[PDB]
Image (cartoon, rainbow, N blue to C red):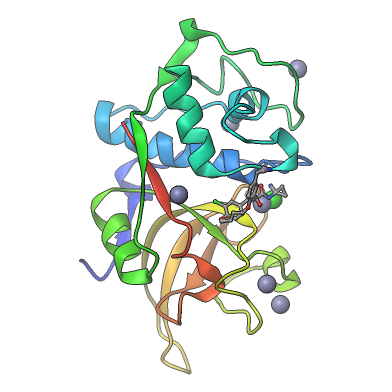
Length: 220
Ligand SMILES: N#CC1(NC(=O)[C@@H]2Cc3ccc(c(Cl)c3)OC/C=C/COc3ccc(C4CNC4)cc3C(=O)N2)CC1
Ligand SMILES: [Cl-]
Ligand SMILES: [Zn+2]
Ligand SMILES: [Zn+2]
Ligand SMILES: [Zn+2]
Ligand SMILES: [Zn+2]
Ligand SMILES: [Zn+2]
Ligand SMILES: [Zn+2]
């Protein structure tokens, strides 16, 4: 695997979005991964409808604004046989009756792949596949108010992941402690959070915040 990867500059990543007052991080993590793979496939970058996931992926076991799983969204897409674009079915940070329209579908998936649950397996996936859906332990105020730098939180749990985000790459930086490899992570809380909406999460410090523990991508 290369020492550095950043899919953003290869055109694989849409603008940072803001889930707002809806517990939909899983849906943003899911669209971002599907967006990267549709782009690998068609050469076209099209924003996908989180709302469409929020409103409709209930039979796959998502709970709308009360939460869900990325795997669950990928199955939805597969079972549904398509997914509407963002602009055909725009995001409203609530849940409403399913409004899916096959006419505006712009994306599909044939399933999904779970990646082996350690960081080296994740690095290869990110290197060869593209943006990868992951959950982290985001339940600490240091993360809620993250600004800049490699994020490292001492009581983060490798087992207590609570928040789906999107690994768009990875690399390295100079640091006083020479722990300076990071994962490049796209969040769904707005441009004003982190570094334009992104956080650098420590990498190869013992699966920090459990980033390698629940990582998957859809197959298109
Ligand atoms: N925004 C936001 C909120 N948070 C979530 O939506 C979280 C995101 C998540 C957390 C850990 C993950 C993944 Cl892939 C995703 O990795 C492994 C852990 C999975 C266990 O978590 C669940 C099991 C099942 C469910 C479904 C049953 N109710 C939805 C939901 C969850 C869930 O908690 N989803 C609602 C506040
Ligand atoms: Cl959230
Ligand atoms: Zn959207
Ligand atoms: Zn509405
Ligand atoms: Zn999975
Ligand atoms: Zn903490
Ligand atoms: Zn924690
Ligand atoms: Zn979340």
